[PDB]
Image (cartoon, rainbow over all chains, first blue to last red; front, side, top):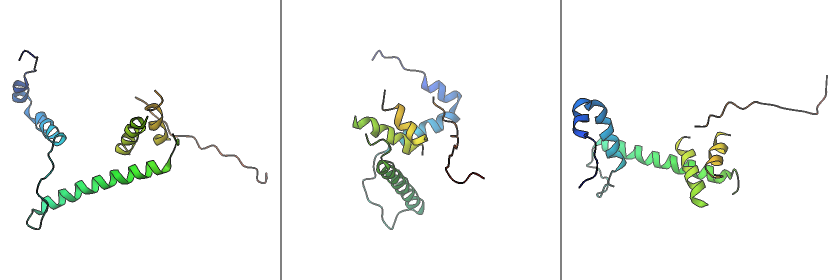
Length: 91
Length: 31
């Protein structure tokens, strides 16, 4: 196609241990949602991880609600949306 | 102050915030 791409194959072949977590992070950024619902025939690890994801979402939503309810400045919607997302994600 | 400062520099367009000093006054009885 003519575009420039780095030699990812040689980098994996020389330093595969780092690229394991690099690929795992890249997969975790782009994860499709589960089409079928969770049921009683699923793995115990599966329900634990589902509960962990739901608890993470609920913690983020609760902290978002608390920071929005405090109304620190009482004041560009995307600006304080991104800033509040940052303060929740590092709080 | 940490959550005030994050909502400050990203809206009115690294930063390290030290531990804030407690200063207190009063008008009670002076022994």
